Image (cartoon, rainbow, N blue to C red):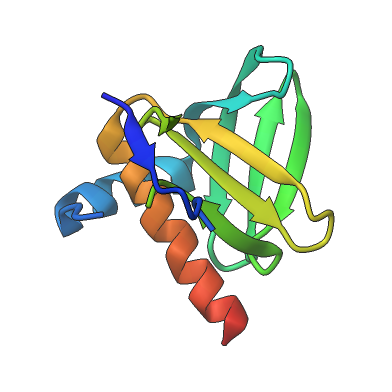
Amino acid sequence: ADLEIGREGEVIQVSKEAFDNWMNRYEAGDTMEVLFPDGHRIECNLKIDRPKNFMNLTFNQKVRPIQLDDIAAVLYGSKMLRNPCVVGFRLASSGRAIAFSFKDITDAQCFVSFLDDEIKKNQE
């Protein structure tokens, strides 16, 4: 069921065990979808390297690398609606917004928490 967003706009209680599992999978590399403005998606592999402060999107042997340092915002809730599986975030460098869709809500909410930590770090 859709999240309903406040008039103000978009500018999480997940278990630690769930996060730890999420984190292990995607550090290994695991599957998600990148949303696009025209509304099509592509199935990618998302691999997080915490030491290197990058996360790599692999599609068709093509890798869009994202710097963890780069992440500036996470968009996930507060008729404006968001499917719970879909997480949007903005990059500081491009000023662009990207949407990942995860295989379930839990995973999405983990990516939200992971993003939150990186953002706090980045703000120092």
